[PDB]
Length: 252
Length: 252
Ligand SMILES: NC[C@@H]1O[C@H](O[C@H]2[C@@H](O)[C@H](O[C@@H]3[C@@H](O)[C@H](N)C[C@H](N)[C@H]3O[C@H]3O[C@H](CN)[C@@H](O)[C@H](O)[C@H]3N)O[C@@H]2CO)[C@H](N)[C@@H](O)[C@@H]1O
Ligand SMILES: NC[C@@H]1O[C@H](O[C@H]2[C@@H](O)[C@H](O[C@@H]3[C@@H](O)[C@H](N)C[C@H](N)[C@H]3O[C@H]3O[C@H](CN)[C@@H](O)[C@H](O)[C@H]3N)O[C@@H]2CO)[C@H](N)[C@@H](O)[C@@H]1O
Ligand SMILES: [Mg+2]
Image 1 (cartoon, each protein chain N blue to C red):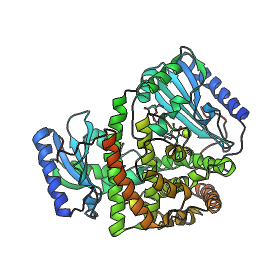
Image 2: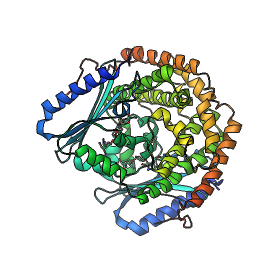
Image 3: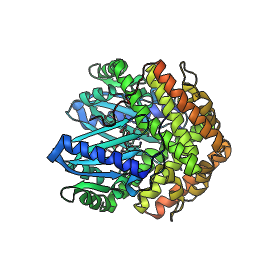
């Protein structure tokens, strides 16, 4: 019957019950336990699931328990300090959506400031890593989407266009977030927060209005909006120095 | 302003240049080279990218080169035989979308039947792996989506509902593909092929109609369609035995 309505108090009880269970089972291998996500920001809605992180001392520790009771869902990730710190300092194309975890840490157990160290690492990532992630995003994702919607324009199918438009709008949101080196609060607010930022590529806000309103049935307006956004990207990358190497047929 | 229009003959010319370049650089470390994706089953549209794969003899080989010339995009993955076969034999929630690669391999170099060996491995995966992936999908993705759209109904934002509905429809497509052990052709045909399968959970095809048509502006009809799909999931999982024990507050 799906998730039920729960209050913040009930969630913190579950959190502290899980904390006790983790300490009973693993004992001194537990370096730190925190809550992240919406419950960590104390923004959590009545239906939100629970996300917790655990720093282990045992080397190469990397596992997780993800379950539901039928009424609520919990995910607990267990990582060694080294594994967690490397993850916090790696910038992938979906960094603005995944690494909000490290800017929403609610500590409930920490034997040696480990969670603070993870937070510091996540916020001190070198600027060059965001630059590379932006160039990789344009090649590995945006360029590929451009071929996908241009294929639709000539040979269809248009039934993929609304889903692909959503993907392009989400990828554009990642590109902006990588530029500003900021993580989005929640998944539901990614597009709302993306259009309120500075230095938007031309055509991005117009494209997002289709995705946020759900008016994705006019394929011609979508294709025309995607091309304008695709065009706006390339002046935007030159204006900010995110220059993509296009000089070789084969780069190895 | 790429990607540009290309013919199959122009793509195979680029492919064989890369094959020549791969053999020049890595020589006898190359066990096999193949083309997958749309060019692999030679359906490729006028704008499709080029996807290639390489089997290496080097033990820990796992790297990729992904680039564009401004006109076309190429991705070449280099994997040891052990790494590639283990990947082909592991079933994640996005198996129906990622592992079609292994059912579309066009060999252009193969020193010892390595590519046929990859195809055999990918198609002989134990039924238990698909069963576990289905149960994990329902918990890790579907249950989480249900909480998210129920939050939207109570506290918004409505601007996330069209994007979240697309995500739910794609997760349902994964659920169907894992059930029937089938991989989807391309990203563009995932939804069309998913709704043509048997044993659909009640409410999925109706939900896909909103996503495929792009009529995602009636949040009220979307939430009702999402709930109906969510109900159909619980009957569908019971009828096929994709049952997870949910009786414990903490299952470890
Ligand atoms: N190649 C065999 C195995 O691949 C894995 O990585 C897989 C996955 O993470 C990785 O995903 C990569 C991303 O990361 C990278 N940032 C952009 C790139 N386009 C994407 O590639 C994949 O996603 C694309 C669609 N978006 C597809 O067009 C493409 O065919 C597909 N290879 O591609 C691999 C799938 O083939 C592991 N690296 C390793 O277990 C072994 O190498
Ligand atoms: N935990 C720290 C690091 O996590 C990484 O994996 C990351 C990522 O793949 C992984 O993704 C996992 C999946 O895989 C798994 N099959 C289902 C699970 N819902 C999902 O979890 C993630 O996606 C959810 C939304 N769908 C989010 O609600 C959730 O907060 C998020 N942790 O979450 C991790 C981020 O926390 C690496 N394993 C490793 O570098 C290190 O352990
Ligand atoms: Mg989660």
